[PDB]
């Protein structure tokens, strides 16, 4: 009561695209507030309800709920054009009056056109040299966060304030990036002029995030939902550095991105796919480059929800799962895409790693090591049956139930939900 | 029990140098583990016990305790030379076998010599232009964090691994900074060669931070202490941006810098000076540029614990205090330097801000606004008496007790400790 109302969190336990948009949407139906705390439009959250399919990137997935306000915390990095582009895309799909239910924290940073530009420049520059890069989405997320750290970036509040002072700051930040990539050209006045538009357009939805969020957690009880982006192993600190994103997708990112204390955090749900996927470059212990990987890739439709780039696929990997829990402290799990395994006669799942006939004690801080480990697999009987229609724990068949426990057990975290489809109803609740 | 043992946190509520080193030391006597989660040697924590005076920067203030292990989490940025320089400085002061009780998280980033260099370059470059800069400590903290965000920086684990691959990465990171400051010269082989030394020297204290910290919080009960650096209004997200430091000094930084979940966080203590001080550039609502400021400056010895640069001083400011609590969620307060006010006949303390005869509703996201506010002051009777010897709540005189309540009340947070001196015993405990 004195502490306040506690926040419910939905986070990624692997390398993103675990189905956070799906889980968030299910819990949002109730929610008074749904918000984002980290990342930018590099994120890609797909929601499927009553026949329509959405794909949000900056917009909180609860935006769909008219009876709820959607929030974008200070931790997030926003690319104005990209924001509106996304809104338009969804408006022409049924989304209406979203503006009246969207709130932008005035402390969040801005992804400027050139940030996205140098991001690409940075990638090709890495390829043309090492012949190996990160595999960024080229949305400037990296550069924006690096600008933020340097305290050179610009924030929503700076945009609404005196444009003259803004334009000066803008001028210098642009000239600075050009110093890194003297090839990078920037049409200052163009962007600047378009920015003034965006400013006056974004202005009504902007507010003090700290105050806003504080008022909501200490006033009359409210159901607040925090939608995480990316995932645990993509976390700037704990992920497979440097093959990660530039924000803390782990639980700390919630306090960082919204400005709320730990006691105001309640249930922390770890969304975990029934198998593993990674879109960018970097170590992937269980990766299956064969007919299996192809099957998962195809039955799971694991491809660029925009670019069409198929994602790397592999078996379930408990090492990353447990390491993710050590950092996040999940209160319960969301096990998604079980239906994808309905076909397999037997399912393997990585339980531990060993370097030289030697089982390593914990997840490697050095990603380069992770790339040289031999994983020990456990082979589990498949249930070989269609579960897309299961809606209760008893609908699921033997091996299927055992597969849930298996995950539930080796992670020492109970599974609260089981996903068997993309839509809101294609979900089973264990308790 | 299932959750684990909870961590005690000590954080800054103003603009740093509130006396965290003092509070941490008092609580460390007990502690099994004392650790740092953010910042670098830019920090400056002074401890005074049994006649000796210390000033740590990277070394956790509990280092003094032989019966305890000192930890440096992944969130921190380490400058090897600076680390050892500090250790030596303290060894020649009584510190012995610290190496046997210090542990470095293998995921923390490295502040390279050039980082400190470009930091200075960046400052002068800001002065020679705008005639206004940040007032950094010139320790590369900023550049290191910007490298980290870009995923270009290097970590402890990268240092211990194949030096050949390290040296290559190093080579490129250095050439990159030179592209920003083509004036900046870097003796690659020199630093590189010295780094190999540091590597083999730091090697024995390095360990997997996530695992280490996890084992300690879920195994047999332990008393773990987290020593925060800098302070709330210096927080990269919530402080007076851009006039802040490049890390999250707020509570989220604990989960970010150590990799521990929110439920593993317990008491969060806000250290608050009985008056306000800021060392660098930026808005300072209550700043007193006169005989008062001089008095506080002199009775409080508020000067560079190294450079000798006197710090800006001003009355207590409740606006920043409450805003700090909104973000940190202090479980109790540590009110330091009460003795400094023993002389004043009457003490003023800022209670709210008003822009144009209009009282602003909350702390300004835009620092430039904060610079144009007129604060409303409350004048409180001084106790005019020496409290340096007070050790119990009843030792303190009337107006003194009322001053504590005043803070305790307007912040809606109980004051757990009252500081009346620099030493460990110069402290009163209210409960
Ligand atoms: N068949 C099936 N697809 C699912 C399930 N859960 C989620 N999906 C789909 O898997 C994809 C995951 O991609 P994505 O939306 O990026 O997840 P996010 O990034 O974590 O929000 C989406 O297209 C979802 O519709 C499930 O239980 N079954
Ligand atoms: N007189 C007096 N000095 C104090 C008290 N508490 C702390 N100090 C001193 O105030 C200074 C604060 O600077 P600093 O060590 O940077 O604090 P930190 O950066 O928060 O650890 C130190 O020199 C302390 O010894 C107190 O109650 N009374
Ligand atoms: N929406 C996303 N889904 C999955 N992985 C992502 C997503 N956005 C970024 N990543 C990963 O994050 C890493 C860094 O890319 P970026 O986030 O663009 O800086 C890469 O390995 C990407 O594959
Ligand atoms: N040890 C410290 N004590 C107080 N303020 C600090 C300290 N270190 C950095 N700051 C402040 O942090 C801001 C950014 O400097 P830096 O932390 O060096 O990037 C400046 O306004 C400094 O005054
Ligand atoms: Mg996605
Ligand atoms: Mg200090």
Image (cartoon, coloured by chain):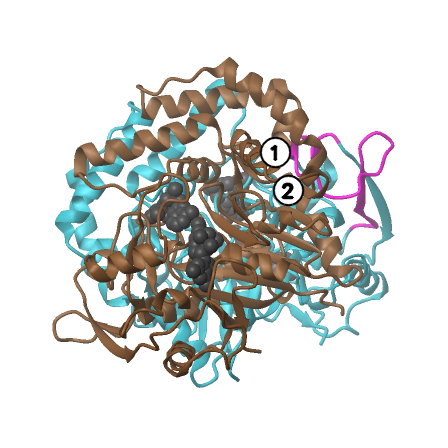
Chain colours: A cyan, B brown
Query: In the rendered image, is residue A140 in sight?
Result: no
Give percent across and percent down for residue B380.
Answer: 29, 79
Range drawn in magenta: A344-372
Query: In the rendered image, is residue B298 in sight?
Result: yes
Residue at horizontal 71 percent and vertical 76 percent from the top: A431
Q: Quadrant of residue A125?
A: top left
Magenta-drawn stretch contains A207: no
Q: Mark 2 points at which residue?
A: B105
Q: Does the residue labelled 2 lie within 8 Å of ligand 4?
A: no
Mark 1: secondary structure:
helix
Residue at horizontal 19 percent and vertical 48 percent from the top: A166
Q: How many marks?
A: 2
Q: Quick one: A95 or A227, which is closer to the camera?
A: A227
Image quarter hosting the C terminus of chain B: bottom right
Mark 2: secondary structure:
strand
**Label 1 with label 2: CB-CB less than 8 Å:** yes
């Amino acid at each position: 009561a004195a502490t306040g109302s506690r926040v419910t969190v939905v986070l990624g336990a692997q390398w993103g695209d675990e189905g956070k948009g799906k889980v968030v949407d299910l819990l949002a139906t109730d929610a008074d507030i749904v918000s984002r705390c980290q990342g930018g439009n590099n994120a890609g959250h797909t929601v499927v309800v009553d026949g329509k399919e959405y794909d949000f990137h900056l917009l909180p997935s609860g935006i769909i709920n008219t009876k709820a306000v959607s929030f974008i915390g200070n931790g997030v990095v926003i690319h104005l054009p990209g924001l509106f582009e996304e809104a338009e895309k969804n408006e022409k799909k049924g989304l209406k009056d979203w503006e009246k239910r969207l709130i932008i924290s005035d402390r969040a940073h801005l992804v400027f056109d050139f940030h996205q530009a140098v991001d690409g420049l940075q990638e090709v520059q890495r390829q043309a040299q090492e012949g190996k890069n990160i595999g960024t989405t080229k949305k400037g997320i990296g550069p924006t966060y690096s600008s933020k750290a340097a305290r050179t970036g610009l924030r929503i509040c700076d945009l609404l304030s005196d444009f003259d002072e803004f334009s000066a700051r803008f001028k210098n930040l642009a000239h600075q990036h050009q110093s890194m990539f003297p090839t990078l050209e920037i049409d200052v006045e163009g962007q600047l002029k378009r920015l003034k538009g965006f400013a006056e357009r974004i202005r009504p939805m902007v507010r003090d995030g700290v105050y806003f969020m504080y008022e909501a957690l200490h006033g009359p009880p409210k159901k607040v939902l925090v939608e995480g982006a990316n995932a645990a192993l993509l976390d700037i600190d704990f992920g497979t550095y440097p093959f990660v994103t530039s924000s803390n997708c782990t639980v700390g990112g919630v306090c960082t991105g919204l400005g709320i204390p730990p006691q105001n955090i309640g249930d922390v749900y770890g969304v975990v796919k029934a198998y593993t996927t990674r879109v960018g470059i970097g170590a992937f212990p269980t990766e299956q480059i064969n007919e299996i990987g192809d099957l998962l890739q195809n039955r799971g439709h694991e491809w660029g929800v925009t670019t069409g780039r198929k994602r790397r696929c592999g078996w379930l990997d408990l090492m990353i799962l447990r390491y993710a829990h050590m950092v996040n402290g999940f209160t319960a799990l969301a096990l998604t895409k079980l239906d994808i395994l309905d076909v397999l006669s037997e399912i393997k799942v990585g339980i531990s790693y060993k370097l030289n006939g030697k089982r390593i004690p914990y997840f490697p801080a050095n990603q380069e090591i992770l790339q040289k480990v031999e994983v020990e697999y456990e082979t589990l009987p498949g249930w070989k049956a269609d579960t897309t229609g299961a809606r209760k724990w008893e609908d699921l068949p033997p091996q299927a139930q055992s597969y849930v426990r298996f995950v539930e057990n080796h992670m020492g975290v109970a599974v609260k939900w089981v996903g068997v489809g993309k839509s809101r109803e294609s979900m089973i609740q264990l308790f």
